[PDB]
Image 1 (cartoon, rainbow, N blue to C red):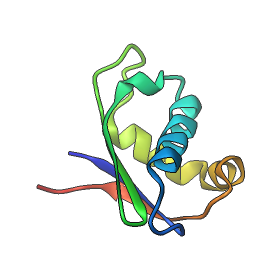
Image 2: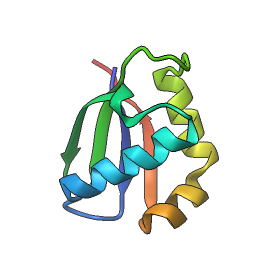
Image 3: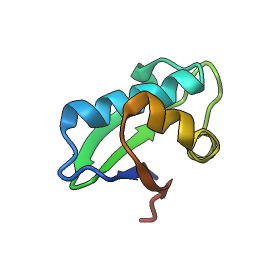
Length: 88
């Protein structure tokens, strides 16, 4: 399952999806290398969390994103409109 974050930017630049994912990784103390398959789709960025030394899961990433939304928005300079985990 992938995580996703929908922003107010469209199309979201690849470079910007990457920065936003890096911001989220920092909140969780995991290197950005733990996020794989990073891709932008319209206004959204999507990603997979691989197994890591911090034991951070896909749901932990979603929760940290909700809990720190305002900080992420300040750091990134964009708005987050939705976040979640996808379903096959």
